[PDB]
Image (cartoon, rainbow, N blue to C red):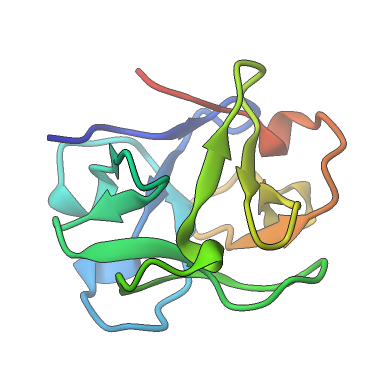
Length: 126
């Protein structure tokens, strides 16, 4: 199924730019809508999937590491702990899904960053 993942601080949704299906495409914030590029399904394997067959994927384990779409393979960089406080924590990195530079505008990129309970690190279903 899946649905929107909205950033608390920005009021904008986790969005694959231009509805690309290309592996390595970095995620962004965008005004929320019903496009398939904003529908994320949480799986039992700990994934957040878009298009049914692409995984939310941490390209690295450090602060500033890009968060991208990528073909699913079961790796720990494609697993996310969905905490009750809105944080979305990468299993491999222990870092939070984070809107780059505390940005809120359309096109703000998504990265990993130290969990700090920031509004740019809190994510809600709608």
